[PDB]
Image: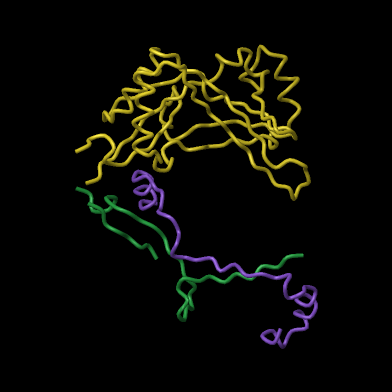
Amino acid sequence: QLRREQVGGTKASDFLEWWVIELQDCKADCNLLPMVIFSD
Amino acid sequence: SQQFDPYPLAMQFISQYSPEDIVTAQIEGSSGALWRISPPSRAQMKQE
Amino acid sequence: SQQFDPYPLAMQFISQYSPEDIVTAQIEGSSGALWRISPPSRAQMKQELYNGTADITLRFTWNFQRDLAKGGTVEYTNEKHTLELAPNSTARRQLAQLLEGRPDQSVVIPHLFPKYIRAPNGPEANPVKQLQPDEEEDYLGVRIQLRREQVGGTKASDFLEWWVIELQDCKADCNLLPMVIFSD
């Protein structure tokens, strides 16, 4: 998801941007990406 | 362990590691910093 | 091979490497990300360029990252070609003007972009002396341009900036900086 925030004749590149990624199946944990990692 | 029941595979692999030997990375998605794209490059990306 | 005819030097050096052992880095110039300079620091930079006294530097560092899966003991190699911009010299006198945000003006700096770089197993990516005798005059000239985009009582630090560098002799490849790099 591209969250977008206005600052202030371009309407596109006039203001802030950033990216937010979530798992496809998020129940209430949209701020969460678990990633189990194995260490030998 | 109990969520990979059908599988002897888990016994071969998962069992090798003590439960503390394995960690999780609760990486957040929202707190990505502001994007850095120059509007020429953003326009070219949009074109492509 | 055929573009270094006079030279037995090429036979000694270039021949050592299979043609696939040598790769090119089509690094783009336009797609540099937005500049990050705090307007105190930008103003201080402008001051040092405008009425500076101590001689200033402008370095240009490359850095190659290889893969360890193919063996090897080093992962990063790098070096720099430091250049000095004399006070009241033309180069600085034009960079300073460039910083004021004029639309189309630009400057060219000579001897800044070596073309053939050896990447041996040691952390010294030394330029190959043996395709270029001068070691300082055979370097290419690069063309720096400050592209500038408005957003919106300062007229200077109110809006976006970024840098775009091109070779001095660009035919139609302004988005191209070839850089032949040698791998042992």
Q: Is residue C142 above or below residue A10?
A: above
Residue C66 lies, with reference to residue C60, above or below; the image says below
- Position of the C terminus of chain C, as image quadrant, is top right
Q: Is residue C50 above or below residue A31?
A: above
Q: Position of residue C13 (x, y in %)?
A: 73, 22
- Left or right: C82 with respect to C169? right
Q: Residue at x 77, y 43 (%)?
A: C72
**On the picture, is A10 further left or further right than C145?**
left
Above or below, comparing residue A33 to residue C6 in the picture: below
Q: Position of residue C125 (x, y in %)?
A: 67, 30
Query: Which image quarter holds the N terminus of chain C?
Result: top right
Classify residue C153 by image quadrant.
top left
- The colour one sees for chain B in the rendered image is purple
- In green, which chain? A
Q: In the picture, which chain is yellow?
A: C
What is the total number of numbered labels drawn onto the structure image? 0
Quadrant in which residue C10 is drawn: top right
What residue is drawn where x is 73% and y is 65%?
Answer: A39
Give left or right: position of C81 versus A25: right
Query: Residue B21: which quarter of the image?
Result: bottom right
Residue C71's spot in the image, x, y percent? 78, 46
Q: Quick check: C74 left or right of B46?
A: right
Residue C94, how many percent across, how many down?
A: 35, 19
